[PDB]
Image 1: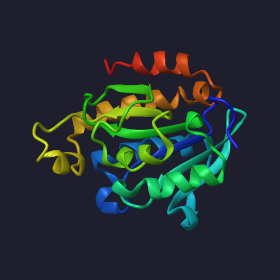
Image 2: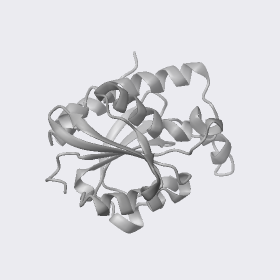
Image 3: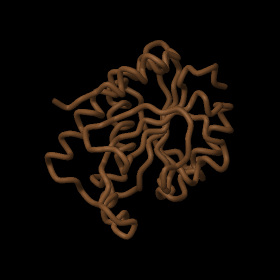
Length: 196
């Protein structure tokens, strides 16, 4: 299984299908797909765990990657059995997700806490508890609770997309620290990111 707070499972949250791939609620997918490309980790079909998953070496550590294909609000139907099967404790999991409460171009690493209204995290925390790490990728908030659907299921304008893309790229460069267990340093260096 996992070992200490070396990160050994990186999950990206999102919805399946081309109609959702460019939407804000897929920010976690964007990060994990880009991470998989950086390190040459194949993301392959994983019907057993209702997802797409991979395994490979990141900086000398054996790491698994997971994209649930459940739809966002059923994400725990993938993450929970996968993490349990591979004996991965929450403390060794990083979940990348869109964050309504932060601006586009802001990105933070958080350990613990609740779902903050995120319907994918809501499906996960009841099962494994809160003590996993999160890569919170700012997407902004549309105002009212009404509008949250269109917001997250929208395609950001180009300036916001650029801001998010630069923050995601920055975070990719800090995964080495995370797989090495250097969570405090990673948190400082991720949270310090500015777009300009």
